[PDB]
Amino acid sequence: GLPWYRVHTVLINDPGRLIAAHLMHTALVAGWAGSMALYELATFDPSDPVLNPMWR
Amino acid sequence: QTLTYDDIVGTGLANKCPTLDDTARGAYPIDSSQTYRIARLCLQPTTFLVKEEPKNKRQEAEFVPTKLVTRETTSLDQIQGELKVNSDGSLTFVEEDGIDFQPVTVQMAGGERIPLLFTVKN
Ligand code: CLA
Ligand code: CLA
Ligand code: CLA
Ligand code: CLA
Ligand SMILES: CCCCCCCCCCCCCCCC(=O)OC[C@H](COP(=O)(O)OC[C@@H](O)CO)OC(=O)CCCCCCCCCCCCCCC
Ligand SMILES: CCCCCCCCCCCCCCCC(=O)OC[C@H](COP(=O)(O)OC[C@@H](O)CO)OC(=O)CCCCCCCCCCCCCCC
Ligand SMILES: CCCCCCCCCCCCO[C@@H]1O[C@H](CO)[C@@H](O[C@H]2O[C@H](CO)[C@@H](O)[C@H](O)[C@H]2O)[C@H](O)[C@H]1O
Ligand SMILES: CCCCCCCS[C@@H]1O[C@H](CO)[C@@H](O)[C@H](O)[C@H]1O
Image 1: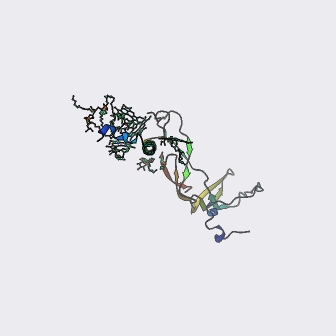
Image 2: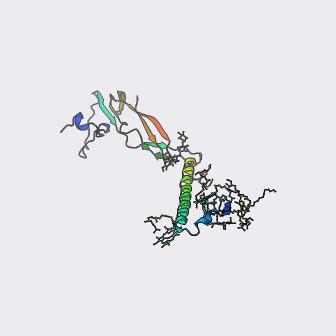
Image 3: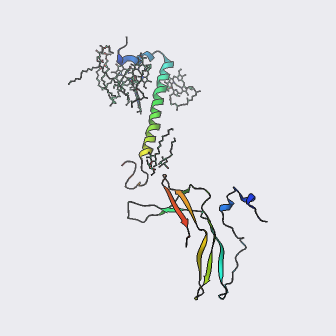
């Protein structure tokens, strides 16, 4: 069968499933962004933008 | 003219002090031979400010605005006491009794809740 490093090649001639894979990728990236921002809000201390800004 | 409990109940007006007309710019004579009292003192807070506490200790901390979270339960009222006329013609109010405190919780930016006993006791 297909070697492990070629599994996604099944999409090359299947535009609908390629779009589905792409949709999944974008869902994952956007969920990362939402999750990342929530984790940063759970940890960020806003009380000192002078000596404790976001980049510290 | 005058409101009953049923007119007031649940409106918020019970937590408000009485107001006077813009017309009320008069003068109330004090006869220094007469004794006086305050029969009703009412205090309706409209803003609570809390002094932020810096790490800086350089530059003075400001008083910042806060959000009231305990609803219309903040005013002091039905307070009474003697209004003394002093020998130099100054008046001194000596609080005796009344609804002279309210626990109040206000919330700062970012969530810190600051309870206080808002009061004029004694
Ligand atoms: C954007 C990511 C993504 C997308 C959209 C796809 C989509 C596809 N894959 Mg690929 N794949 C991926 C990443 C992805 N894969 C990764 C990271 C691996 C290595 C694990 C694989 C290995 C793989 C194999 C071996 C096969 C496919 C196959 C397929 C097709 C059918 C679905 C399937 O069987 O998935 C497989 C199911 C997964 C890959 C689950 C991913 C494992 C993650 C890490 C678990 C996530 C759970 C949770 C949210 C997070 C836990 C993290 C941790 C803190 C514990 C489809 C085209 C099949 C096929 O069509 O081949 C011809 C197939 O046999 N994929
Ligand atoms: C848009 C970017 C992109 C896309 C859509 C693809 C898509 C494809 N690649 Mg290419 N490729 C890319 C960039 C990309 N590649 C990059 C940057 C490199 C160098 C790293 C490669 C090097 C490469 C090789 C050497 C091969 C492909 C192959 C393939 C095909 C099969 C992939 C597969 O089944 O893996 C299945 C993968 C797994 C089951 C697991 C991989 C797990 C990795 C190593 C670790 C986990 C990654 C983590 C989940 C992802 C976060 C990503 C983010 C940080 C970027 C498919 C057409 C294969 C081919 O041509 O088939 C004929 C092939 O041999 N790619
Ligand atoms: C006017 C026609 C039109 C428009 C507006 C688009 C727009 C888009 N196409 Mg292209 N496409 C078109 C014609 C069009 N396409 C034609 C005729 C073909 C040949 C059939 C393709 C083949 C094609 C492929 C093969 C792919 C795209 C993808 C994309 C998207 C990539 C950006 C993205 O996902 O952002 C993120 C998305 C958003 C911020 C959401 C946008 C809001 C959506 C679109 C509303 C959904 C409702 C709508 C009625 C459903 C169908 C929309 C459809 C017309 C695109 C984007 C929505 C890629 C994609 O889908 O990846 C996920 C992808 O893989 N297109
Ligand atoms: C420009 C931005 C960008 C681009 C071009 C890509 C491109 C890619 N992404 Mg996506 N990704 C992005 C941003 C991006 N990503 C962001 C911001 C997130 C949120 C964190 C993700 C989350 C994400 C997930 C969860 C997955 C992808 C996967 C993929 C691959 C799907 C095609 C494929 O089959 O590859 C075949 C695989 C390769 C060609 C190898 C890529 C090797 C990368 C470049 C370096 C990984 C190196 C190292 C071994 C990582 C080990 C991690 C370990 C320490 C845990 C492709 C290389 C999917 C994938 O890799 O499936 C196998 C996958 O599961 N991405
Ligand atoms: C965030 C989400 C994260 C989830 C992702 C997790 C999935 C990651 C999967 C990675 C594993 C892939 C390894 C497959 C390994 C594997 O299948 O190898 C054998 C494989 C042979 O392929 P063939 O084409 O012969 O196909 C046979 C098929 O049966 C394979 O599917 O070759 C490759 O895969 C090419 C690249 C690997 C070559 C690596 C060899 C390493 C040598 C040893 C090094 C250590 C010793 C060093 C000493 C100094
Ligand atoms: C599917 C693609 C994945 C590629 C990832 C490569 C990253 C390395 C950076 C670039 C150097 C490339 C030199 C390749 C040399 C080259 O030209 O390769 C091309 C080769 C495919 O070539 P062929 O199609 O000719 O197949 C040759 C096979 O038949 C074996 O003989 O690609 C692979 O073998 C893909 C697998 C490499 C996998 C490497 C190990 C990944 C381990 C990940 C550990 C993850 C831990 C996760 C923890 C949660
Ligand atoms: C979209 C669906 C998913 C939504 C759910 C995910 C929510 C994540 C939101 C993060 C923002 C809230 O972040 C959270 O805030 C409070 C208030 O400072 C912190 O709480 C901390 O300080 C407060 C106030 O002194 C203490 O009473 C508390 O015990 C202590 O843990 C949390 O440690 C922090 O992690
Ligand atoms: C998508 C909905 C996420 C849920 C949001 C939680 C409320 S918002 C949250 O409030 C905390 C307390 O006031 C703050 O300390 C923190 O900075 C703020 O991000």
